[PDB]
Image (tube, rainbow, N blue to C red; front, top):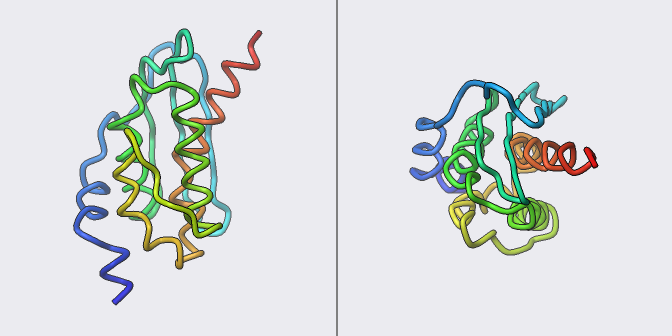
Length: 144
């Protein structure tokens, strides 16, 4: 089927229930990431301390896969370490581009994004939320 494997029931439930949409009051870093192919955009607001994410907010205007991926991030990002987030982003890259395994731990819900591997046109939109968070981490780290 592939299409029903891509737009599964979990993917459709994620995209429809995105939490923490908006902006943060006094964020430590703000990253905006754009997919030039499809025109999808994700702006992520992040607060951190001692290597741990303490607050999160984002504004999403992406396809269903980008919405579903941003929904999983908003449910599991608070309380995660920078190493946990880079590992999930690293695992997401290797799953879609290198036939790698699905991420695990607090990002085990990305297993439902495995059919997107054979759908190259949606790879950028799905990774928008991961690259926006990693850019905020890189900003807060650079401030030293």
